[PDB]
Image: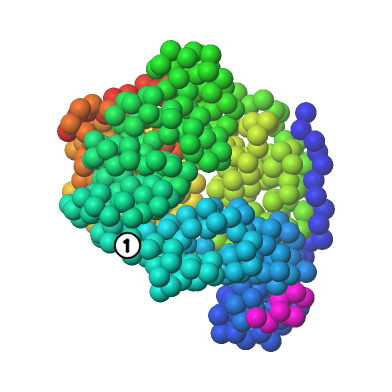
Amino acid sequence: DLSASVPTRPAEPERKTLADYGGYPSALDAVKQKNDAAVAAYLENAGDSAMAENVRNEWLKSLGARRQWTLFAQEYAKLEPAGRAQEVECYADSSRNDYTRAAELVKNTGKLPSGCTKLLEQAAASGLLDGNDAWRRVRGLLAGRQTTDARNLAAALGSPFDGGTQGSREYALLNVIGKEARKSPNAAALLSEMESGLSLEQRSFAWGVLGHYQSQNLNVPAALDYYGKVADRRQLTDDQIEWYARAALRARRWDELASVISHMPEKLQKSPTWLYWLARSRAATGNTQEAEKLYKQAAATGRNFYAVLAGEELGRKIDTRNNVPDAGKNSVRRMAEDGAVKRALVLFQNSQSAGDAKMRRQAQAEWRFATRGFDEDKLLTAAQTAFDHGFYDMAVNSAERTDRKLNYTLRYISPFKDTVIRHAQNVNVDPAWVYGLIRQESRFVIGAQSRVGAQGLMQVMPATAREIAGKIGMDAAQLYTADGNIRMGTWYMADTKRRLQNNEVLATAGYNAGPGRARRWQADTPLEGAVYAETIPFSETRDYVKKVMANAAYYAALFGAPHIPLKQRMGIVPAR
Ligand SMILES: CC(=O)N[C@@H]1[C@@H](O)[C@H](O[C@@H]2O[C@H](CO)[C@@H](O)[C@H](O)[C@H]2NC(C)=O)[C@@H](CO)O[C@H]1O
């Protein structure tokens, strides 16, 4: 059974929730304006809410930047630890001269928030950083065009870019590893020329930069040539070493793939991606028992693309039967009386009645806040509460967070079947695939709006909507209605597929990145579908295709169509 236990945090009246929200954007503005008195006034009588936690975190980032440490410590003491932002924890630890977090943070080779960047610079200056990892970060920052941060870290390490020592040499290497320099037809030739005067670490990193650029440009032979010159693979950034694995994968070099994976950080080796591909490599080289152990490990990672593929190699088909009962209705009712859950529901229902999309986004924040500490039974109760109130994305948000207790009908909800199934049938596309795409694009939020203006359940861009409307006799603004949105998106799935050799994997990539890109990523030979997906150069699209296709496998199982293994759904991507 599922436990009937629900939280009973103090509830506030709707009026109070709405009054607090009325002041929430101004409180964030007051942080930006450094109006500390106004922020304090907003927080003074605030409920214990995500609104308060969000304002307090943003305030603390500003207080830490401005070195107002007494006010910082006072307010930091009011945040729950699971609620403290990364940059706020870094400012707090810096204020106590505590550099414990540095050992892990320095392994990041990309841009970090200012508080965390400064924590690492302070650790460096006190000799508290691993030298190998510190200089790897300096190199990473140079390659990612974060030159100021690179410069400041090198200085803190005691070897500044103008000091004639290590720092100056790493900076000079920009003639090879720069953003544009790495693309030069002469980059490899220039690196080969200056190589004798470079350290083992600088040479390894620099070939990794060149290999990465080729690999992401899908010049696999050149990528493997340059990556083959990396003598110390642990010097590579995470993105560089994954792109070495991707090149070996694309070339079907199973032994080289297995070798590269074994040099990855443990965190990357234990990812579903590299558990599964190492398993495939062991299988391809006749190591059946090692393959099986790895497939089991990948299948244990839950509800995702590579876990399903790994299960299939083990003879396990997807199974969407729930392994827990429905939550009891009294518990579903009483969950909505918890003060933090209620607050989220108040903001959600008022966002609907009032047509306030910003309010709806804060309602999502209240939901995540309210459910943050929940055990699996409370998550599944709360998922049904959210579904009943029409808060569909939060129903999925809570249901998908479990590990052991699995409710697939709440993980893979299918509202709007009286519209989506018909539109999908009308252009002859698989409705499980459409649902899989909607779940990834909008999580069934009908008015969803991306950072760049993609709109609605299927996240069609306005420029694309205008083009589609011109082809199928619609008006462009029907993009912003549910029924028009589903008609546009399903038609565009079918049209994009028609334009990409009728292949569903290519179509999924083309829907997100444009068909011209999807076609650019094909090879001159056929590719296994999962190999095309894993070697997509755009990180967002690569993630997107795997999620949409895993989603589609789960929906197909709930919908009861004849069984299609995910491996079969991925199939073979044709040669260009
Ligand atoms: C669903 C949606 O709107 N998707 C957008 C993409 O398909 C869009 O790609 C661009 O779309 C146009 C229509 O096919 C093309 O004229 C344009 O060439 C195409 N880009 C190509 C082909 O490379 C991408 C961004 O380009 O964003 C999606 O959200």
Looking at the rendered image, the quarter that the C terminus falls into is top left
Q: Position of residue 149 (x, y in %)?
A: 47, 68
The vertical placement of 35 against 9, above or below, is below
Query: Quick check: can you spot residue 317?
Result: no
Please report the bounds of the magenta region as a residue range. 67-74
The vertical placement of 521 against 282, above or below, is below
Looking at the rendered image, the quarter that the N terminus falls into is top right
Near mark 1 (Cα within 10 A), the count class, few <14, some 14-19 or many ≥20, is some
Residue drawn at 20 percent across, 27 percent down: 525
Residue drawn at 77 percent across, 75 percent down: 74
Tell me the element at label 1.
helix
Which residue, as the protein is rendered here, is positioned at the far front?
A: 196
Q: Is residue 13 left or right of residue 25?
A: right
Query: At label 1, which amino acid type do we have?
Result: Leu
Return the residue nearer the eye: 428 or 538: 538
Return the residue nearer the eye: 410 or 147: 147
Toward which corner of the image does residue 562 lie, by quadrant?
top left
Disc 1: which residue: 174
Q: Position of residue 121 (x, y in %)?
A: 57, 68
Return the residue nearer the eye: 243 or 571: 243
The answer to if 94 sits in the magenta stretch is no
Query: Quick check: can you spot residue 325?
Result: yes
Residue drawn at 55 percent across, 34 percent down: 270
Q: Position of residue 407 (x, y in %)?
A: 63, 32
Return the residue nearer the eye: 344 or 260: 260
Q: Position of residue 265 (x, y in %)?
A: 53, 41
